[PDB]
Amino acid sequence: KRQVASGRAYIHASYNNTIVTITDPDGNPITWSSGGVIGYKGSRKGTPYAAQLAALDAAKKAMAYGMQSVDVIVRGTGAGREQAIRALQASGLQVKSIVDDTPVPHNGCRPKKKFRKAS
Amino acid sequence: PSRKAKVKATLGEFDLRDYRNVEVLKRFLSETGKILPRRRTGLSAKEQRILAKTIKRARILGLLPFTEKLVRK
Amino acid sequence: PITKEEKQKVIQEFARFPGDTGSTEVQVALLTLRINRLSEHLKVHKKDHHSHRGLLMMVGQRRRLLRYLQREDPERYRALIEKLGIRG
Amino acid sequence: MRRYEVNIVLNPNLDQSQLALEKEIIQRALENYGARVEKVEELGLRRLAYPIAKDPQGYFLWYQVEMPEDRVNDLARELRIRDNVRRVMVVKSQEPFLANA
RNA sequence: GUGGGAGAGGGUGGUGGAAUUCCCGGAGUAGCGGUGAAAUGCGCAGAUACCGGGAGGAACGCCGAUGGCGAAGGCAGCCACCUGGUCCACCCGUGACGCUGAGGCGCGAAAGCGUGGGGAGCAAACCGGAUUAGAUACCCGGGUAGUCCACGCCCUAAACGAUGCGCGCUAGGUCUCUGGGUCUCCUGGGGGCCGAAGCUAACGCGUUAAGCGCGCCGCCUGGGGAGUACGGCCGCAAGGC
Ligand SMILES: [K+]
Ligand SMILES: [K+]
Ligand SMILES: [Mg+2]
Ligand SMILES: [Mg+2]
Ligand SMILES: [Mg+2]
Ligand SMILES: [Mg+2]
Ligand SMILES: [Mg+2]
Ligand SMILES: [Mg+2]
Ligand SMILES: [Mg+2]
Ligand SMILES: [Mg+2]
Ligand SMILES: [Mg+2]
Ligand SMILES: [Mg+2]
Ligand SMILES: [Mg+2]
Ligand SMILES: [Mg+2]
Ligand SMILES: [Mg+2]
Ligand SMILES: [Mg+2]
Ligand SMILES: [Mg+2]
Ligand SMILES: [Mg+2]
Ligand SMILES: [Mg+2]
Ligand SMILES: [Mg+2]
Ligand SMILES: [Mg+2]
Ligand SMILES: [Mg+2]
Ligand SMILES: [Mg+2]
Ligand SMILES: [Mg+2]
Ligand SMILES: [Mg+2]
Ligand SMILES: [Mg+2]
Ligand SMILES: [Mg+2]
Ligand SMILES: [Mg+2]
Ligand SMILES: [Mg+2]
Ligand SMILES: [Mg+2]
Ligand SMILES: [Mg+2]
C-alpha cells in the first residue's frame, strides 16, 4: 500500500541462514524473507538454494508493492550470499549497484571461544 | 600480486608529514578506508611508518575515511 | 627537562678551570642535577618504575665517582660534598 | 616555549556574527594561555570523510604558535569548552619530511 | 662535553572511530538462533533482518613485518605533558675512576587475596539442552566470581634462546632495521638465514659461538619416594622460599 518502485535490498548471510530485507530508499523495511519463511527448518536454511528461494520470495513480495529497481547491500560471509545476489540478478527486479557492508570491528569486543584465536 | 603500479612512483615530491593534504594522502588508502601495504605504496620502512601516523592524524580531523563500503561484487 | 643553558651554567660552575667539561667535579654536579630532577619527577608518578631504575643507575654512578674522588683527593671531596649538599 | 600547530573545526552552519564571536573567543583563550601566534590559515568549510556531529562538512581553521609547554593541554581543553567547536588537535611542529628527492 | 637520530621503553591527562550489549523511536511479521543432526533458549508483551537517536564498558582493524623498544616480566588508535635507556658523528674534557657480585633492597605475565568502585563482551563454578554404554567432558543455550580502575598484598611459570654477566681473539656470503660518510659502495650499532676454522654424543653451534681464552656469580652429582615430611622465615589467606 505504498508504491515505492525504487529501494534497497539487504542480504544478511550467515552459515546458519540467509535473510533478505527489502526496504524503501530511507531504509525502512517493506518486506522480508528468510530460509525459514520458506518451508525449510533445520540446517537446510543455510543452503544456497534456500537463499535463492528467500531472495525470490522477498522480491515478488516487493514487486507486489510495485518495486522495480533496487540497490543491493551484502552483509556477512556464508553460503547463499552470492546465490542471493544471483537470484536477485533477474528476479524481475533491476539490480543497480551491489555493495559489501559486512561489519567488522577494530578489535573492540572479545569473541566467543568458538570464534577465538582472534580479537 | 598487485604489482601493476606503485603510489610513490605515481606522484612527485611531497611532504609525508603534512596531514592536511587530502589529495596526496587519498592515493595511499585502498578502495576501502584501509591503508595500503608496502608493495602497493612502494614506500620504505621509515616512510611508511610516518605515512601511517599522518594518515591516522588526518582521519581524526575528518579529512580521511576510517573505512568505506566496497562496491561492485 | 634540562635546557642547554642550565647544563652550561652548572658545567661552568663546577669546572676546575675554563674549558673543563669532563672532570670528576663536573660529572658529579651533572649527575646531581639529573638525580634531583628525576626524584622530583618520581615524587609524583610513583607508579613509574622504569625511570626509577634509571635513578638507581645514576646514583650508583655518582657514588662510584665520589668514592674515587675521596680515594684520590680528600680535600676536593669535602669541597664537592659541602657544595652540592650530598651525604648530609 | 615550543612551537605547536593548533587545528580547529567549527560548525559550517554558523553565520558571520557567531563565527566572528567564536574566533574572538579562540584568539582570547589563545593569548590567555600565553601563546604568541606565528601564523594562521583559514581553509573555509570543507567536505568531511565521515559526518562529524551530524554534519557532512566542517569549517577548518589552522594556527601556528609558540607557547609554554605546561599550559598546552589546558589551552586545548579551553577550546573544547565551546559548544560550536567540534575538533581540536594540537600538534608539535616538525620539519617537513619529503619523498622522491 | 658538543651536535644529531630511531623507537608499541615508562608514568599522568585528554580525545577518535569501528563493533557488541541495553534503552527510546520508525518501518515491518513469523520466525530467529544454533548443530553432524538437533533440543534447550529467545519471539504476537511484535523478536530476527533494516533505519535514526541515546547510554555505557572494554579493546584498538588497515598500517603490521621474516619489524621496533625494554634488564626481565612485557609494551600497539591518536594528542600533549613528565621521564628512563640507547646509537652515531667530532676526538674536545677527566685520567684506570674498571669487571663481577654471596646477603640486602627494588621490579616482577596470568591466576589468586583485601577495601572501594565499575561491569558492554567474555566466562571457572553453577543451571540447563544434546551426544554417549555412562558423559561430573568435548558441542549448544544461560551464567556468578573474575576479566576493567584505584590503593595495598601475593613472588609463581615451558618468567624459554630450556643458552649468567663482561672483555679480547678466530673466513666469508645473503636478507633486514637504524646512524654517518669521498653515498653504485665504505664505515658503526641491532635483528635474521647459510656457512671457514673449530666445537659437539648426535642434533646442531659457528664475529648475535655451543669456537679460542681470562675474571666473577648461580647451579648439577642415578630413578621412584618427593618438591613430599619436619623445622624455620615470609603471607590476611591461598600458599611461597
Ligand atoms: K630454570
Ligand atoms: K604468621
Ligand atoms: Mg540453520
Ligand atoms: Mg630517491
Ligand atoms: Mg611509547
Ligand atoms: Mg524497536
Ligand atoms: Mg496478536
Ligand atoms: Mg550499564
Ligand atoms: Mg635489549
Ligand atoms: Mg615473550
Ligand atoms: Mg630520550
Ligand atoms: Mg682528547
Ligand atoms: Mg692531562
Ligand atoms: Mg652489578
Ligand atoms: Mg604479579
Ligand atoms: Mg591480575
Ligand atoms: Mg579484587
Ligand atoms: Mg558455555
Ligand atoms: Mg555467554
Ligand atoms: Mg564479590
Ligand atoms: Mg620460547
Ligand atoms: Mg650477518
Ligand atoms: Mg650484524
Ligand atoms: Mg649489520
Ligand atoms: Mg667443519
Ligand atoms: Mg650455521
Ligand atoms: Mg637412591
Ligand atoms: Mg634419590
Ligand atoms: Mg616426579
Ligand atoms: Mg609447589
Ligand atoms: Mg615448583
Image (cartoon, grey):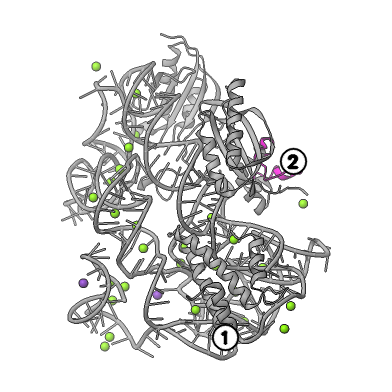
What residue is rendered at 55% in x and 70% in y?
A: C32
What residue is rendered at 72% in x and 74% in y?
A: C18
Residue D33: image location, x then y, percent: 58, 42
Disc 2 crowd rating (10 Å Cα; few below 14, some 14-19, many 20+) is few
- Whether labels 1 and 2 belong to a single chain: the reply is no
The residue identified by callout 2 is B11
Chain of the residue under label 2: B
Q: Give the spatial CA distance, label 1 vs label 2.
A: 69 Å
- Displayed-image quarter of ligand 3: top left
What label does residue C74 carry, if any? 1
Q: Secondary structure at mark 2?
A: loop
Residue B17 appears in view: yes
What label does residue A38 carry, if any? none
Q: Secondary structure at mark 1?
A: helix
- The answer to whether residue D7 is left or right of residue E88 is left
Q: Is residue E13 above or below residue C6?
A: above
Q: For this rendering, which residue is in front, A63 or B56?
A: B56
- Boundaries of the magenta span: B1-24
Residue B37: image location, x then y, percent: 62, 47
**Amino acid identity at mark 2:** Leu
**Amino acid identity at mark 1:** Pro
Chain of the residue under label 1: C
Q: Quadrant of residue C44?
A: bottom left
Q: For this rendering, which residue is in front, B31 or E84?
A: E84
Disc 1 crowd rating (10 Å Cα; few below 14, some 14-19, many 20+) is few
- The answer to whether residue A108 is left or right of residue E177 is left
Residue B72 appears in view: no
Q: Predominant secondary structure in magenta?
A: loop
Q: Quadrant of residue D85?
A: top right
Question: Closer to the observer: label 1 or label 2?
Answer: 1
